[PDB]
Image 1 (tube, protein in one colour):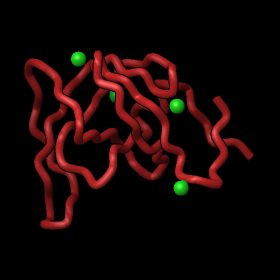
Image 2 (cartoon, rainbow, N blue to C red; image 1 turned 180 degrees about the vertical axis):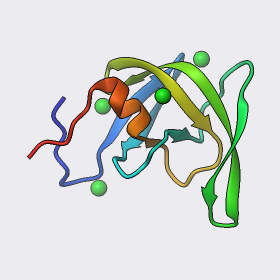
Image 3 (cartoon, rainbow, N blue to C red; image 1 turned 60 degrees about the vertical axis):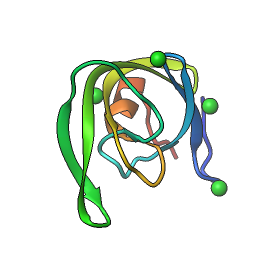
Length: 99
Ligand SMILES: [Cl-]
Ligand SMILES: [Cl-]
Ligand SMILES: [Cl-]
Ligand SMILES: [Cl-]
């Protein structure tokens, strides 16, 4: 799609049977979601949060649909004030900023 920026660029995402929303955030390196669960192994990761650091779970090779487009990549699961799609998945989408 072509998404204008008059409002926050929030899109529908889906991971397995979990339909959620998230912000397309070109200021974020990584993708972090609070309200989904994934099975199996993960690696711990620190991200910045208001105490200093927040521990999240890094899951690799996750199939995710973003605004109806399927990609595969890394998803962090843990506390976040909003669900964020970062550049790691936007690069998998072939997303660009255009003006
Ligand atoms: Cl808004
Ligand atoms: Cl959407
Ligand atoms: Cl699922
Ligand atoms: Cl990735």
